[PDB]
Amino acid sequence: GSMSGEPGQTSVAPPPEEVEPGSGVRIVVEYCEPCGFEATYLELASAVKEQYPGIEIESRLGGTGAFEIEINGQLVFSKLENGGFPYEKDLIEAIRRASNGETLEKITNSRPPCVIL
């Protein structure tokens, strides 16, 4: 298939009021520090703080070229399975579904880790 699909439709804008309604979650981007994946964790760490300054997003270790996302310290969506290509709405809707107080998407882990040759 193609990497493209549903490009950016929204436009830019100035810094809105200062409110952290998304407070109530602890994001934890698990990635291989000693690899060079920070380029992605820093590109969002500057946009996540301007959105939800109330939450708490820290950096943790993964293992090797990994990017296990943990909206609440628990892997809910791996990047080594899909192939990457995240979404600004997928990284922001994490706390919106977690802080909601309702069950979130879980994995049964009935299959091995989708490798890549």
Image (spheres, helix red, strand yellow):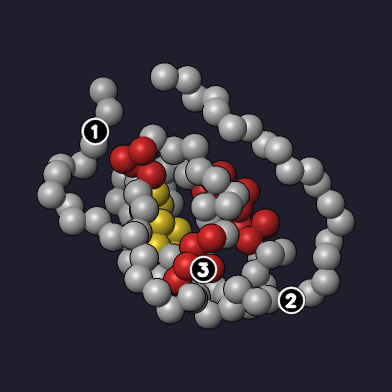
**Mark 2 highlights which residue?**
19
Tell me whether the residue at label 3 lies in contact with that at label 2, contact meaning CB atoms closer than 8 angstroms.
no
Q: Residue at x 41, y 19 (%)?
A: 1
Residue type beneath disc 3: Ile
The tag earlier along the polypeptide, 3 or 2, is 2
Q: Residue at x 49, y 37 (%)?
A: 85
Q: Identify whether 57 is placed above or below 66.
A: below
The tag earlier along the polypeptide, 1 or 3, is 3
Query: Rounded to the nearest whole Å, what is the CA distance between mark 1 and mark 2?
Result: 41 Å
Q: Which of these two is toward me, 60 or 84?
A: 84
Residue type beneath disc 2: Val
Q: Residue at x 59, y 32 (%)?
A: 6
**Mark 3 highlights which residue?**
95
Q: Which of these two is toward me, 81 or 99?
A: 99
Label 1 Cα neighbours within 10 Å, binned few <14 / some 14-19 / many ≥20: few
Residue furthest right in the image: 14
Which quadrant would residue 49 be assigned to in this image?
bottom right
Q: Secondary structure at mark 2?
A: loop
Q: Secondary structure at mark 1?
A: loop
Residue furthest front in the image: 102
- Label 1 or label 3, whichever lies nearer to me, is 3
Visible residue check, residue 12:
yes
Q: Identify whether 29 is placed above or below 52.
A: above
Q: What numbered label is drawn on residue 115?
A: 1
Label count reads: 3
Residue 25 image point, x, y percent: 50, 75
Q: Residue at x 65, y 69 (%)?
A: 52
Query: Rounded to the nearest whole Å, what is the CA distance between mark 1 and mark 3?
Result: 29 Å
Q: Which of these two is toward me, 45 or 72?
A: 72
Q: Which of these two is toward me, 42 or 1?
A: 1
